[PDB]
Amino acid sequence: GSSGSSGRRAKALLDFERHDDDELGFRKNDIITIISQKDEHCWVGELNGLRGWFPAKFVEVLDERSKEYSIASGPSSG
């Protein structure tokens, strides 16, 4: 249906209870949309209508491709 800007999403490997309001917590096996990756160590995603930093190591990156149309293969070795 609708369409717009698409970002990234990291899957939580374990439960992380944010200590500071700035820290973004999450439950084990939780999906969080990455908004601004402060750095290769500290990332900022979105969850429960919240936005805070968190250790990427605690979570895992996800690069999937759905509803793929614009891109496709055709003339392959013939």
Image (tube, rainbow, N blue to C red):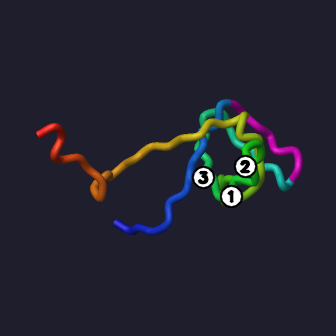
**Horizontal and vertical percent position of residue 22:** 84, 55
Residue type pointed to by label 2: Trp
For the residue labelled by badge 1, is the local secondary structure a helix, a strand or a loop? Answer: strand
The answer to whether mark 3 and mark 1 are in CB contact below 8 A is: no
Q: Which mark is residue 36?
A: 1
The answer to whether mark 2 and mark 1 are in CB contact below 8 A is: yes
**Horizontal and vertical percent position of residue 51:** 72, 58
**Horizontal and vertical percent position of residue 63:** 50, 43
Gap in angstroms between the C-alphas marked 2 and 3: 10 Å
In the rendered structure, which disc, 2 or 1, sits on the residue that comes first in sequence?
Answer: 1
Say which residue appears at 45% left-offset and 68% top-offset: 4
In the rendered structure, which disc, 2 or 3, sits on the residue that comes first in sequence?
Answer: 3
Q: Name the residue under label 2.
A: 43
Left or right for 47, reference 39: left
Residue type pointed to by label 1: Ser
**Is the residue marked by circle 2 packed among few (<14), some (14-19), or many (20+) residues within 10 Å?**
many
Left or right for 6, reference 14: left
Q: Residue furthest top?
A: 14
**Is the residue marked by circle 1 packed among few (<14), some (14-19), or many (20+) residues within 10 Å?**
some
**Is the residue marked by circle 3 packed among few (<14), some (14-19), or many (20+) residues within 10 Å?**
some
Q: Which mark is residue 33?
A: 3
Does 12 sit above or below residue 21? above
Residue type pointed to by label 3: Thr
Residue nearer the viewer, 3 or 73: 73
Segment tinted magenta in the rendering: 14-20
For the residue labelled by badge 3, is the local secondary structure a helix, a strand or a loop? Answer: strand
Say which residue appears at 68% left-offset and 38% top-offset: 27
